[PDB]
Image (tube, rainbow over all chains, first blue to last red; front, side):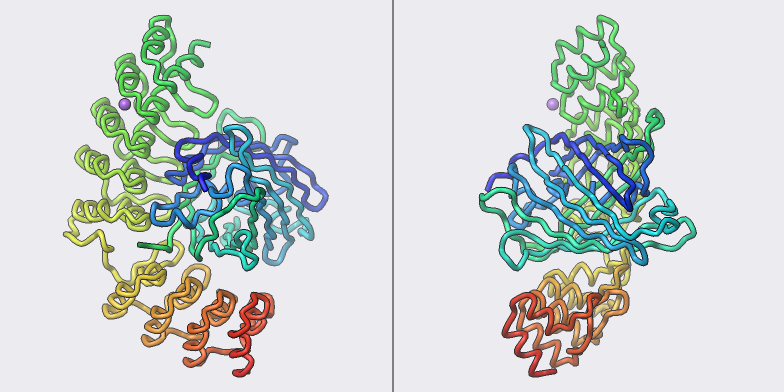
Length: 227
Length: 298
Ligand code: NA
């Protein structure tokens, strides 16, 4: 009922990812702030185990949609905040066209005053000389439309979208995202009418960071339901 | 050590402690490990006395954090009007860019802060600035439902009144290939009709392959489905989409939409990216009446 009240101001964020892609294990930690009133994320991630064995852009979607801007006329359609503070489970399969897939399971919840995203990621069937394991993706990111619908079981939501990764040679690598979210708690949640989010992201580097890392600025707004 | 305390005092609004720390030699341009300075924090959190004293003591008004944000970006987003004005009077770059290429005017338009939009224009904000995804502040205001701001921004660009309801090249498209008609498909029937009457392309596909008819079927708007079809929409559009409008209608249980699609020649044998026909999807989603209709039409 009142989960949205936890997001009226700036909220600290922690992200922890445990990854294994084709047997290459790695860990990523992230921290920063989200300002859901304005759909804004300011985050920095580091690969704490060493070199990241996949391109950073391929992890962006895995690495907190409760910080999406939901405008006032769409407040009754914001599943993500309604599940808080107990949180939700977010599961994906991500199919990289003509390459392997990621499967992920995350818990997104408050731990004290911090919104924490804790993820396990498994990647299989990647080509050692493909675009992912061969690091042929540009260090940049596109704008996407994210499609949201209530699930048929009346428990949570399904989410579908296609991510476009620019390849160094000028082509585009599609990453087809299949997503499901369910509440962790027994409390009531908001099941939305169908709608979409529109995303903007910028990836950068911190000149004083010596570890493999990603600085991320992200702006996300919901839309599609009016008056 | 003094730098950290000054960052905290600025953040918490302790103007008495700010004055003390400065008298003890604190570096007014101290920065944390993500480039945030005391001026950033005071500007973002609305602490005007502290913004003023920091600027008096030489704080860098255009300091950028790791995300490219200046204090003016943060104050324009947070909605602190007098802080915006004070920053501009002390040399803030009115067209500074964050890492997505947003100027302060983009952010105020996005955030719905009309008075700040107007002050930024007064101090030289570029009304035609585009961020890295091609959006002007007008575009961000429109797409966020901030119609009053959109009306102001179109006027400031010399485009006359009426911007609140959209600035009208009926076949403009953004970087994801959305035309005005893609946006109107989400339940704006009168706008769909107006756009088509003024020459909008009914079959424009977005970057994912979706036509307005896909979006109208996904969002369940029967009367919009009907008028798109009346204006020649391809009932079986797929190509890059990987599914047709009838697949979508079969998923979400709108029997009347299925019926008009079939009436207009929708293909019951089309397969989506998983090899499913609309009948298969109707079964999978528990939409039994739709499944029976689709089987009759097999
Ligand atoms: Na104030």
